[PDB]
Image 1 (cartoon, helix red, strand yellow):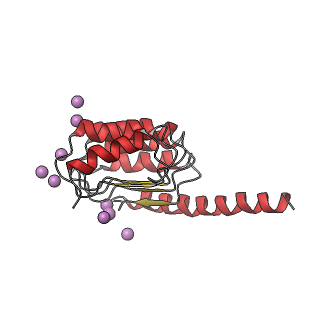
Image 2 (cartoon, rainbow, N blue to C red):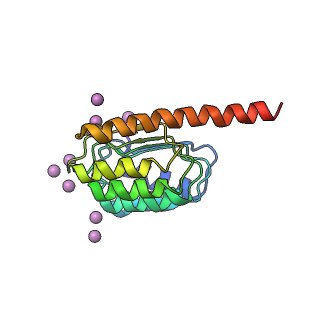
Image 3 (cartoon, rainbow, N blue to C red):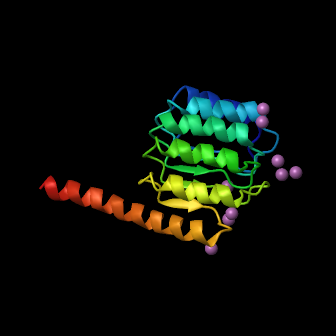
Length: 175
Ligand code: NI
Ligand code: NI
Ligand code: NI
Ligand code: NI
Ligand code: NI
Ligand code: NI
Ligand code: NI
Ligand code: NI
Ligand code: NI
């Protein structure tokens, strides 16, 4: 259904900060140039209306992951990011988790089913990095190592608890 037409036009709309574009979905669109995927990331940096960005199954690679990481350090709007079924490696994934040190607005990240498998050292490091982020509530990924898997689940439950705590101590103290 969507195609290179929509891809160029939607990108313009992002750059223009169109208030009516709250969701960008590129899922399953083939033959998007890597630099076009990068441009999406670059445009989204200062976009104030896009809440969800989904690029699943676009052949996005680490260059795309790096571009997205940069954008994540700046963007205060996107709450849900879908990277499933792409060519992102553990490097691209670490860059994103390092970016999340600087991001308190993204609550859902999913990278299921990458064609290049993450690696244990990367899973161990994701868990270490996630400790420093208190706003991510959902991580779409299935861990190979039982240890990082447990730690990440506990961290996500923690973050869920931290968000209720913040809201409650706002409501309580605002009387
Ligand atoms: Ni879809
Ligand atoms: Ni493929
Ligand atoms: Ni590349
Ligand atoms: Ni390169
Ligand atoms: Ni690949
Ligand atoms: Ni997975
Ligand atoms: Ni999975
Ligand atoms: Ni292939
Ligand atoms: Ni499971």
